[PDB]
Amino acid sequence: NICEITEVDSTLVERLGQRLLPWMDRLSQEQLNPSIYVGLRLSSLQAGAKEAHYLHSLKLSYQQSLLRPASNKDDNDSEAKPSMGQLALYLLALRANCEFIGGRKGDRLVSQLKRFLEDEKRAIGHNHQGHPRTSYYQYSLGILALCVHQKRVHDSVVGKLLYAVEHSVDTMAMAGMAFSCLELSNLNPKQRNRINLALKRVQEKILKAQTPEGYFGNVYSTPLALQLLMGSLRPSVELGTACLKAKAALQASLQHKTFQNPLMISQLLPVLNQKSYVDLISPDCQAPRALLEPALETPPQAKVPKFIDVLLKVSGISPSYRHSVSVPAGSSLEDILKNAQEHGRFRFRTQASLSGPFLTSVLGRKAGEREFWQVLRDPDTPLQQGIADYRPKDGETIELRLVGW
Ligand code: B12
Ligand SMILES: [C-]#N
Ligand SMILES: [Cl-]
Ligand SMILES: [Cl-]
Ligand SMILES: [Cl-]
Image 1: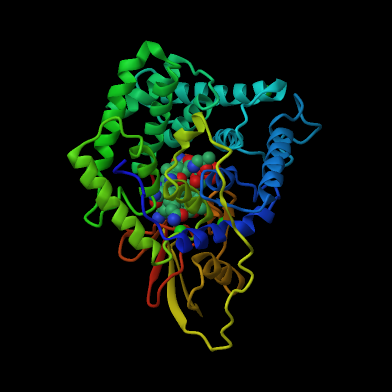
Image 2: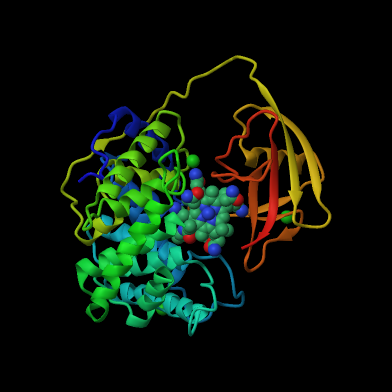
């Protein structure tokens, strides 16, 4: 297949996998990450049988959190649980261990997932003058998660996805893989053709989204795009050119330490191993992988570093706020935030996610329903990394902007 990463440097892949390894010891409820597990299982690498314990931890945690009694004893909260999108990833995790969800606990979780989709269907509405409470990405992911377990969703639920496609890249890829799975599973035969046409659309929109550099959307959307596109069934001259161009671009960024985010790597590794989430229909748990070993040697400087002077600014709220910080080069945006909070009038709140700390509130102003704290480098360039991974450059002005999407 022309859209497959045929050639990759084994030491690059091993470095990437090396970045996920420490996470296999991070088993608290907020650190646990079904996406990392799936990434590794679909990869050419293995993280010890640290893996089995990880999955087992996922099972105990996702069950005890999501299956808690009819009403909790006088709290209405105590210990915030995984979301439904995360449940969908947990289901992908099970398949990656060649397990089908089952038992009474299994049924209850499948139900929770289906209820989620049903509720998103209702939020979207009638004839689509309305948004999903979460997003089309999780909508698609839910469908794909149930599909790989041979679980059928309502024709009306799939309809909502089809319609949204029929009338960015990351969402397209994920919607695509859901459709791709529905087709190969024949779980909604009553819309067999409608789905086939939706795939062609998805392929079209992704190629249209290709940048001068070769990425589909951006470097980080590229692996998911490739996950869907290696699924072929529409081999094309335009598609071959696009895929070759996309691949060169991806391999180039790999030489430059572009992927640092654990979730990103977990989406990349399957691709560098010619696998996608659609392979979870029938996973191959017999294939051997290369054992990753503790890196265990992070090089010591004993030098005085460079410092960077960076300007922090906050907009989209009254009043606006600015802050001057000089910190050691290589410091993350999150470090700069904690610094400003520690040594000044700044304050912020993040909440946990599978991509790490998601900035939810700045200066006591929390983003509401269709708002979010956008992060940009001046002038007006939205960052492509979150606070924990983005390491600002010298001279930069970094903007936390409350936006209405
Ligand atoms: C939906 C989405 C959003 C929504 C989320 C709200 C919503 N409606 O649910 C919005 C628009 C707010 C958003 C914002 C951002 N996003 Co976004 N987002 C996505 C998308 C398409 C799906 C994530 C998802 O639902 N995952 C599924 C569920 C199961 O996982 P989850 O961990 O529970 O998802 C939560 C987090 O993903 C959080 N979230 C969304 N984006 C990001 C980005 C980061 C860095 C973090 C830590 C969290 C986060 O929202 C979800 C919960 O509401 C992904 C695509 C992808 N390829 O993964 C990108 C993606 C994760 N986002 C990305 C980016 C860059 C951002 C921003 C930094 C953009 C910016 N410059 O301001 C911000 C985050 C800033 C902040 N406040 O901390 C990148 C991350 C790349 C990287 N190297 O880490 C991705 C991969 C897209 C891309 N190709 O660039 N995003
Ligand atoms: C996120 N986009
Ligand atoms: Cl239930
Ligand atoms: Cl990254
Ligand atoms: Cl705050």
